[PDB]
Amino acid sequence: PTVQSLSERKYSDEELRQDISNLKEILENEYQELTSFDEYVAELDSKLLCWSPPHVDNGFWSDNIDEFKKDNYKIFRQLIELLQAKVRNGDVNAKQEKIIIQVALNDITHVVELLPESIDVLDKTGGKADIMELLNHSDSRVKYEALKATQAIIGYTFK
Amino acid sequence: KKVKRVIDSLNGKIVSLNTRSSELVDTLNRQIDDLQRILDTTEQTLHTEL
């Protein structure tokens, strides 16, 4: 993100402009060009989810919906289990657990907006309940993401 | 099915129940408050941001 701002403010010096542009390309290209399913699962496995440029991007989620389906979006259900667990075990409101949650809620929101069939998965798992709990919880960023998750389920229940 | 093409043309929303007038009210009040709490969360976040 820092480079993208820098690129805008060009200063008079040919070589400077050249360096800034080259650096913008390399950074951006290297991360995105990984397969989408791969990055998500690698993060899922470690339980060490982080925001990255393709996890705040809608396109990533659209291609990946199909990859999850193996027994009614088993991988999607994996992320829901994973999120539920973090809140309840290892408590909520301590720093480590707080990074994973905000990212996970962001990730879920995107798939639900895109797919109407994932609503079932949240109900079976019990994820539906867990969202409601994050709302009350401290940390502004976790609460924002939680609110966006609630709304995503909500739009679809009533038409 | 032709009365419904009059109602749905000028934006009327028919409410067919066919079960009970006391069993859908519970499942609908279990959504009114559940969505009013999402209002009270997101509007609190709005007034925090403002």
Image (cartoon, coloured by chain):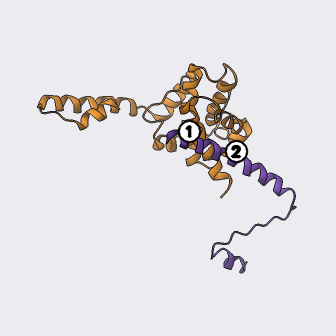
Chain colours: A orange, B purple
Residue A47 placement (x, y as % from top left): 58, 23
Kindly identify the residue that appears in the image at 78 percent across and 67 percent down: B16
Kindly identify the residue that appears in the image at 73 percent across and 52 percent down: B32
Callout count: 2
Q: Which kind of residue does numbered mark 1 sit on?
A: Glu
Residue A53 placement (x, y as % from top left): 42, 34
Mark 2 or mark 1: which comes first in sequence? 1
Q: Does residue B13 lie above or below A55 as drawn?
A: below
Residue A25 seen anywhere in this rendered image of the structure: no
Task: Tell me the number on the disc at residue A120.
Answer: 2
Say which element carries label 2.
helix
For the N terminus of chain A, which image quadrant?
top left
Residue B21 placement (x, y as % from top left): 86, 62
Q: Residues within 10 Å of mark 1 (few under 14, many from 20)?
A: some
Which of A45/A55 is in front? A55
Kindly identify the residue that appears in the image at 74 percent across and 39 percent down: A124
Q: Which residue is mark 1?
A: A67
Which picture quadrant has residue A34?
A: top left
Q: Which kind of residue does numbered mark 2 sit on?
A: Asp
Residue B43 seen anywhere in this rendered image of the structure: yes
